[PDB]
Every structure is written in structure tokens, then in C-alpha cells.
Length: 78
Length: 81
Ligand SMILES: CCCCCCCC/C=C/CCCCCCCC(=O)OC[C@H](COP(=O)(O)OCCN)OC(=O)CCCCCCC/C=C/CCCCCCCC
Ligand SMILES: CCCCCCCC/C=C\CCCCCCCC(=O)OC[C@H](COP(=O)(O)OCCN)OC(=O)CCCCCCC/C=C/CCCCCCCC
Image (cartoon, rainbow over all chains, first blue to last red; front, top):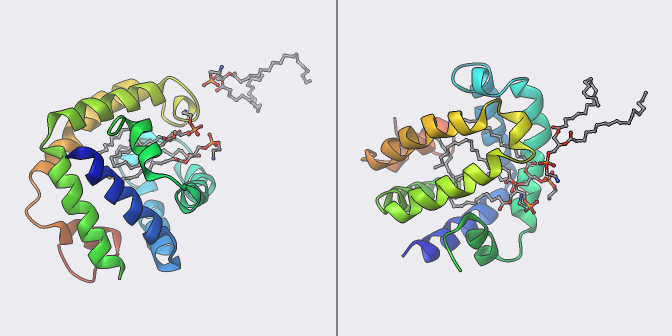
């Protein structure tokens, strides 16, 4: 079933985001990807967009108090 | 630690990509997001980029024999590629 799997993924994402090593690794990977294709071409000013957005997403996943809500927002749960 | 968690996430994504309802739902959500902020401004021609990339990503995850590789590519596991 896709809804239980989505809930598990969101739970894992929140747990993972509560670790600084995760944030550092994802930041370095995305900073690298911003300098090369495909992101270099599909996302202008990629590095600045990353610097601004990645903390927002980290906080978003560190604050969500309802996985089912997110999975419904994406269309995987009712 | 984060390596087992990353492998579990990749395994779940691989499992999900085999169901077509997942693909349709993700397409619907991303088409919605492409028409509004922030993606409307951060991704020029968002809808076309989506139409081109989503199938590639679906296939990439449907042809994955070992999650470790992805987790190694992002730096959460010390080996995999
Ligand atoms: C108005 C300047 C236009 C751009 C100028 C470029 C120079 C750099 C200026 C920096 C600021 C630029 C801000 C523009 C950001 C991009 C906005 C954008 O993406 O548009 C989309 C967005 C809609 O997207 P959604 O929210 O998803 O739709 C559903 C919501 N119901 O709509 C907007 O454009 C945002 C609002 C635009 C504000 C336009 C300003 C109008 C000014 C009229 C007043 C007259 C001038 C006042 C004095 C000017 C000062 C000297
Ligand atoms: C669709 C996200 C990426 C693929 C997800 C794969 C399924 C994994 C399980 C789901 C993980 C959690 C999903 C995260 C997205 C949830 C975002 C959300 O619900 O809120 C929308 C949020 C604003 O929230 P609110 O203002 O409170 O609500 C009003 C709605 N505008 O807006 C956004 O999220 C904008 C950013 C959307 C993410 C864009 C992801 C990048 C897509 C790029 C183009 C396509 C690439 C193809 C990727 C294929 C993925 C397998």
C-alpha cells in the first residue's frame, strides 16, 4: 500500500533531519549539483536558491506533526 | 544511523515507483506546484522540465538493484557505488 509507505518515508525524513550530519551531507551534495548539469541549467542562481531553501525544507520536515497530512497533500493518502 | 535510514527510504521509493497510481499522483501534485510559487519562479518552464524529468526519475528508481549506491552518492553511506 502506498499510504503506509509514504507515512514511513515522511517519518524517516523527520528522524533524519534531526541530525546535523544529514544536513551537512545534503547541503554539500546539492551545492555540488548546483555547479553541474542538470541543476545548473534547470535552476538559475542555483547556489543562492539552495542556500535559502534547504534550511526552509529542513525546518519544514522538523516541524510537521502529521505525516498523513503531507501524504494526502501529495495525493497518497485520504 | 543515517545509512540504514537512507537505504530504507530508497527501498521504499523503489517499491513505490512500481505502482502506477504513485506516478500519476506525483505528476498531479507537481503539475499543481509548477503553476504557483515558489516553483513557478525557481524553475523556468516548470511543466516542461517536469514532463521530461519525472519519467527519467521513475525509470532510474525502477532499475535500481542496490539502494546503497544512491546513499553513497549523497554521502550518507561509506560505500555503494
Ligand atoms: C514589480 C517589479 C517587477 C520585477 C522588477 C525586477 C527588478 C527587481 C525587483 C525585485 C522585486 C521583484 C518582485 C517580483 C517577484 C516575482 C513575482 C512573481 O513571481 O509573480 C507571481 C505572483 C503570483 O504567483 P502565485 O502567488 O503563485 O499566484 C496565486 C496567488 N493568488 O504574483 C506576483 O507577481 C507577486 C506580486 C507582484 C508585485 C508587483 C508590484 C506592483 C506595484 C504596483 C504599485 C506601483 C509602484 C509602487 C511604487 C514602486 C516603488 C518605486
Ligand atoms: C513531490 C516531492 C518530490 C517527490 C516526492 C516523492 C514521494 C516521497 C514521499 C513524499 C515526501 C514528502 C513530499 C514533500 C512535498 C510536500 C510539499 C507540500 O505538501 O507543501 C507544498 C509546499 C507549500 O506548502 P503549503 O504552503 O503549506 O501548502 C499550500 C500548497 N502550495 O510547496 C512546495 O512544496 C513547493 C516545492 C515542491 C517540491 C518540488 C520537488 C522538486 C520537483 C522538481 C521537478 C520534478 C522533478 C521530478 C522528481 C521526481 C520525484 C520522484
